[PDB]
Amino acid sequence: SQTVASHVPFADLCSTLERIQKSKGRAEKIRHFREFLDSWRKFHDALHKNHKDVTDSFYPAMRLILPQLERERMAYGIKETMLAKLYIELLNLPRDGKDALKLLNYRTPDAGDFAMIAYFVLKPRCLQKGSLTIQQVNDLLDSIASNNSAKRKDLIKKSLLQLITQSSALEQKWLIRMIIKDLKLGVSQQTIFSVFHNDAAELHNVTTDLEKVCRQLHDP
């Protein structure tokens, strides 16, 4: 296609995020993040060797890794009780049942947020793994934000059901955390920006062109 995100599955991103969250100590989290960056550039190179000159922008992934910096999309207009009802009819669970109740009676506490509970409910029964790329997830989230800007809760529910019915339980966990806009990764935004930049700079391999260096040192 046109971009790397159109070929990277959303399951790769969700897997990376799950490893980061489950990792203790910054070294392992950072190492998984660098694993994901290296996989990204790897996809870029494979696509170029298959004669597909694609952008190498990481923004389609970074906007999901840092949802609270999301400014291209507007507010999703989704709160956790909507997700409770949604998940409470899609599932065919008994209203005020054992599992079903937990979603309604939820209180924001470490890592005991709504997404964790929804994942605990979805792991027993759910769909055929995942099938959407990062670009398709970004398109569906774009549709949710747009429909919210047009004041159409019905269409919000529509597009989000499109998201859910094509995603595995894990993918739904991290999707929920991306709509609520806090991932609880155990590592800071400052650190993510730092590892991103330091990765680029470490791999830049600046080449000393002595003539260009002379022209640089001779003129401010």
Image (spheres, rainbow, N blue to C red):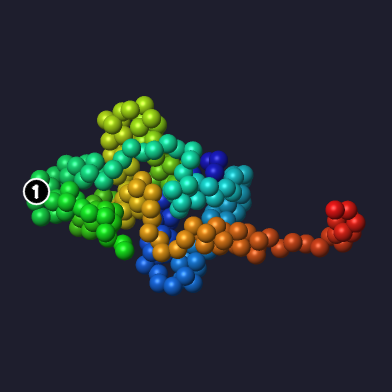
Please identify the quarter of the rendering in which residue 121 is found. Answer: bottom left
Asked whether residue 189 is in view, the answer is: yes
Give the residue drawn at x 39%, y 46%. Answer: 132
Decide if residue 17 is on the left or right side of residue 127.
Answer: right
Where is residue 46 drawn, in percent x and y?
A: 57, 53
Return the residue nearer the eye: 200 or 45. 200
Say if 61 sits above or below 197 in the image. above
> Mark 1 sits on what residue?
96
Helix, strand or loop under label 1 = loop
Give the residue drawn at x 47%, y 61%. Answer: 188
Give the residue drawn at x 13%, y 51%. Answer: 101
Where is residue 99 drawn, in percent x and y?
A: 14, 54
Where is residue 67 drawn, in percent x and y?
A: 43, 48
How many marks are shown on the rendered structure?
Answer: 1
Disc 1: CA contacts within 10 A as few (<14), some (14-19) or many (>=20): few
Please identify the quarter of the rendering in which residue 139 is found. Answer: top left
Decide if residue 184 is on the left or right side of residue 153.
Answer: right
Decide if residue 87 is on the left or right side of residue 37.
Answer: left
Return the residue nearer the eye: 24 or 55. 24
Asked whether residue 123 is in view, the answer is: no
What type is the residue that disc 1 sits on?
Asp
Give the residue drawn at x 85%, y 53%. Answer: 220
Return the residue nearer the eye: 197 or 93. 197
